[PDB]
Image 1 (cartoon, each protein chain N blue to C red):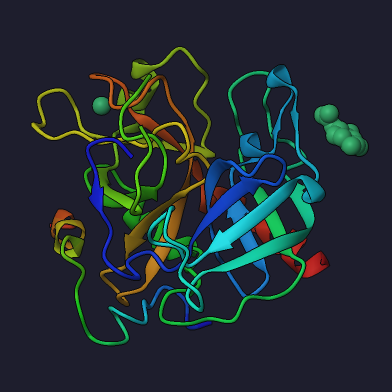
Image 2: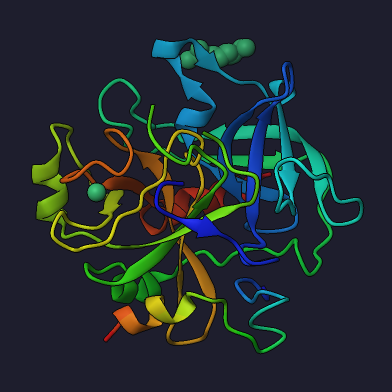
Length: 27
Length: 250
Ligand SMILES: *[C@@H]1O[C@H](CO)[C@@H](O)[C@H](O)[C@H]1NC(C)=O
Ligand code: NA
């Protein structure tokens, strides 16, 4: 319903130390 | 996890731990997909060649943990299970095809800053992201190297390998309900899951909506972080139709 939105990251508007690596791979 | 590192506080809030009750030992990793449903791999519960056939009464589940040692009061929750649902066509006698399982908790878990469910992929999500080259994320408290257990939850970021590369790297019949991931010998990077990370989640962040989708379930592999060998994962989407029926029937 409100899944996959980490309360300490996505909700608080913060990136985890290595999530850019993932999004970067889509390019 | 092999060649992975320590997770951040509440980095994988859907991360679950499957325990045996007597004695209390780490079996597999798992994932929270709703208030009452957990999704691990079938081989964790049922593997007859190793006299493995677990009842609901045999197992325990721990959600919200960071340090496997340190018990944190109103952070981590320990739940027991009402019923277990292994795939009817789970092939243990040949290739670990349809290696999926569902666990209904005896009581729903309240969500927090540390307990939170993951998204299950859709038609479009799976077709667009389940493509070779893209990196996903494996997580678990399994062995740090092959035959060595970690304190804090481990995390590795692994790229999806081309289906023909997966096929030619093993002797086992790879089915559409499997996908593999890992770095190639000349990719200059390493990492894999190990004994204990089975049943665990392979996730991805949707560039479309910033939501974490669970693409796979840590299924099988030949060793841990072996050169020319890749990790095999249960193709969650290919079985979403089954996941739905068990959730909607119970
Ligand atoms: C597992 O055990 C239960 C009873 O404890 C039985 O109904 C089931 O058929 C068993 N399955 C296998 C493959 O051993
Ligand atoms: Na490898």
